[PDB]
Length: 139
Ligand SMILES: NC(=O)[C@H]1CCC(=O)N(Cc2ccc3[nH]ccc3c2)C1
Ligand SMILES: [Zn+2]
Image (cartoon, rainbow, N blue to C red):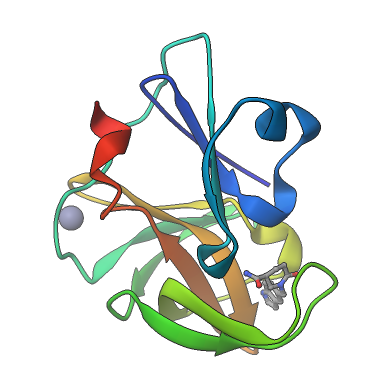
């Protein structure tokens, strides 16, 4: 679990969005596993606007942060889960690191701000849904 709070927006994994997120929907994209909802309170976070390929993510299944080198956002095949059929997930960044399904929502950050959130993983892999291209989150 986890979310990004920026301005009057809340960014969550689309597969973990609540009834309240859907009732306050701003934008969602199944191919990216993202959903953005509106909030009444002003948010705690800053979005990175950069091309960093290193950063640090929070891993809830270890209660720890880990440094990572990750790929640029791209279209990657993701196997079927209980939430989606087998498909290509877009705007996904992969890195070597520990992750389990419940780690989804953990933030990846660089020196410039929030880069994305945990969305996928495998045997020693962790995948992050990028949010740096969503310029409208800042206004
Ligand atoms: N973005 C997606 O399509 C998600 C939907 C929710 C989901 O359970 N998965 C599978 C998954 C996620 C993180 C994982 N970390 C290590 C194994 C593992 C497996 C894929
Ligand atoms: Zn950066």
